Length: 123
Length: 124
Length: 125
Length: 124
Image (cartoon, rainbow over all chains, first blue to last red; front, side):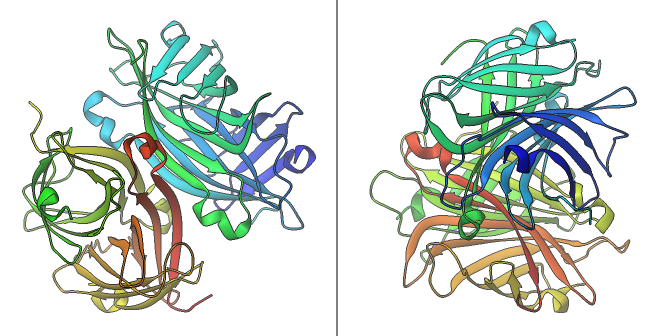
């Protein structure tokens, strides 16, 4: 999964996830969203299980993007939680949480939830 | 500019300990120790926060990840917390979280727990 | 088991009012009044609960739905609460919820909010 | 508006069967049969939908609940699906769901699974 996870991935929206998996469990890279209040690349950091089970299970992982870069600041952050599944049609299947910074009176509606599936090939 | 407000030791309602450093570049680095679950001692965390939040009283958006592997245990799972920091006398980090376990394909429909943790600067 | 415990008026941390009847057959019926959002007055709710919960001290699983349309407003959205009832001197219903808004396909990635509400038998100030 | 479009038999990606009647008043009634999990045969479901959806091409919001007790099994849990119906040649109901199991207080942090199901009018 070190070599399997490292590289360029694309989700069903056409967003681009560029990641390097380190031997120590680290995830580092950039994310470019095809939708939303976003332009160009944003820093991402995360972690993955660097010694997954040998029983055919996937490899658990997660990462975060704060939606601030040199071009825009959406005052929000998304975390993706999911698992990498290797093989001919490799995939990273995730669920995600997008929290906006809000006032206290708006906090009940601060967080979106969704799900993204990443594949090595762009749909 | 919540670098100083976020950096430090935080505790959630379960008694877990979140130790974080906020970097000027938006980085979150540190350790997490869960009071519950398949866990022992500290685990590495990394994440990101909005280093230039709005100045209208809104909170500061942030998130981080722990993969539950350390030198003592490997639960083959990862949790991400997504939330916002609220400064002030009773500073808080209010989060929702997703915990995904590595599964076979047949078990993937039940791979992911959801919950919510509130962190404060004083422990329960 | 908890028909009488669940039936009644409950309030969450936002000051919303959840009025429910638990039927012997597992049904939940009632009305919801949200203190926040694109809502006024009462909306119909329906749901289900475990009418024969475990006897080991576990809570009682339940859930319900509100579609945010009534005679006054239509927010073109629906919220589902999923949770458990915990009986005792300080009874509580602890939930997580999903609010989905009807969207076009291009907006569907941002259709769904998630949150958490705790309901008690006495309301906040 | 979508009473006739929603009413009927639907199937998700797991092969589960969702049988629903949409009432003129916004009610949803029917049965659910899960292809996976601690489940056998049909369970009662009830829910609600927007009976006067927007006319700008948006989907129709809806949700429903199953408590996983029937004459055969009791899993002491309930699932709520929250989502929208999208009409047309390939009609679909896209949902996210929350499955809460009754737990003791010490296990409540891990009480709730989250997932997503897509329903179509023809089985995979």
